[PDB]
Length: 325
Ligand code: NA
Ligand code: NA
Image 1 (cartoon, protein in one colour):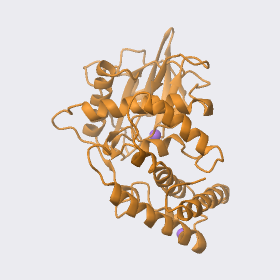
Image 2 (cartoon, helix red, strand yellow):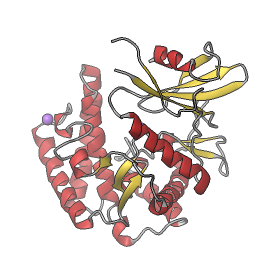
Image 3 (spheres, protein in one colour):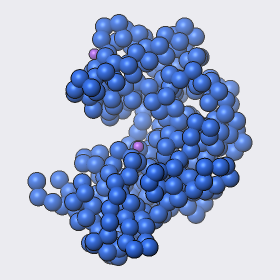
Image 4 (cartoon, helix red, strand yellow):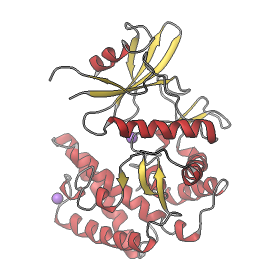
């Protein structure tokens, strides 16, 4: 994808011979572009995940967040013809590219919020929810959904968690029972406008870049590429991506909730669904892991993640879905 990034440079005012540094951000290939003093960020979208109008819809939310919310987000750099999404075609399908202004914290080594910063993540998430709830979306807005069907049902976007390495007979029993309880809890919770709407859907600590390691600093939310319709509190599950099994989960939750409630109400019935959303994220990430596992080395990691998913499932089942610790 480096050659795609180079092709894309010709569409921007930054020199075509600018240096490119691959950054450790996003499932897409994202590069720090350096042209003498100038720094900027080039995102090369992976193949087949979005159509261009969907990317344009993400960028429309970013534009509204920039002007109408207190959340700091990326600023798009238009191409030389004014367009926001550059599509480039090599031989052997076309690839979409978006160019952003430099973000504090993106220069290697990339600096983001840490495990000490769940509260700040919660507060920023509440601000994203508040904006989403009041924003009148453009005509023609289009983004995909993180509903049951597209997570765990008939059209799973990251594949089946059942197919991951390490997910055998005993694990599939535990995980299916907990999944089915989660499904029933989600059906009861419903998808009314107070509970479901436009979300970032990847609000991991690593996606909030900072210009300082000490609080009171500029925090930029990056990587809106999974944004779409889903449960608002699924964003909390994403906050603990890959770390759901840590014994500190309860402390992290309390910190995140304190930050969230500083900006937006978090009612008891929503707080009571936070473990469900953690478990939803866990199954999704187990599916993602399985989709990208096909070796002995990858298998050991999937095996261990599957085992921690089962420990969480047992806690979920024994508490009737109310607790993971
Ligand atoms: Na992502
Ligand atoms: Na299996």
